[PDB]
Image (cartoon, rainbow, N blue to C red; front, top):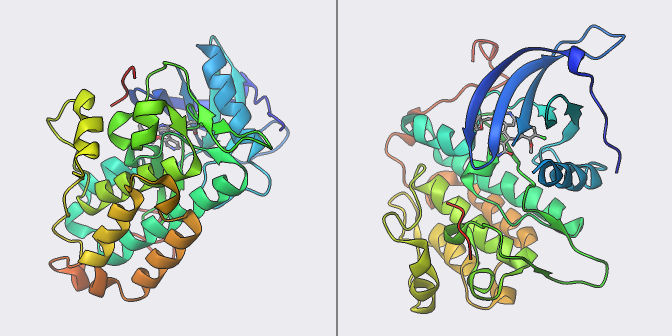
Length: 300
Ligand SMILES: COc1c(Cl)cccc1Nc1c(-c2ccncc2OC[C@@H]2CCCO2)[nH]c2c1C(=O)NCC2
């Protein structure tokens, strides 16, 4: 694990992008020393130990890396410790699905599911439990390419360890598996539960899970056998994937390797698996196009 220290004087045009539970994220241009290459970058800050643990996890999983997992370029030491990554120009996938709903087709939704399952399979191979998978922590590099971000709650499992036992710190109940809510146990299979909630958010075009329901009632709702509803665009095969992700027995949930396969099978005939009105006449910018340059957490 190697952390690059990118000089403060090397960054220009730093401007705010947004704020929330993740802290503050800005956009800027990193001009590396001794070379002329103005790189669009995203800068995050918030507790300076919590942001350094995020950097360690990200650097530990950098080699070989994955196209669908955010890569840490380096860190910067200004008044606070800042994280630096390649800027994802289209922003957060949760805001992207809400803004571009009337132009997102079935091919895009099923490919995003494939790409998130690919990045999660890579993280599982590196013994990394993300613990915060949600549409808010999936970014859009191009409309056709998404990346998993935010390793604030992510934990590397020890060689012998199969699970992480968390402290009383704030965690996202409505995205968490039932064993994480009751016993604070986090595994790659608990991430499969959160992956299913992320898919439900994409399929509903950014709806809030368990909207209006308090988080203190979720364990009870889940123990009664109740789950997030069938999104209107989902055929039964897509919804059964989400429902297999939210099974009580963690081992019975699909594996990220199986989700890559099942959603890739769906992406080969996307209009069979998702019924979207006006799907054949929907378009989003692509780097292939000549005009591409124009374009929650609670105390347990
Ligand atoms: C953890 O990876 C990062 C690093 Cl190392 C540095 C800067 C940002 C991020 N990621 C994030 C971006 C981000 C990364 C790349 N390009 C643009 C970005 O912001 C897009 C919009 C702006 C406001 C919310 O997201 N946006 C978010 C994270 C995050 O960790 N949590 C949720 C919000």
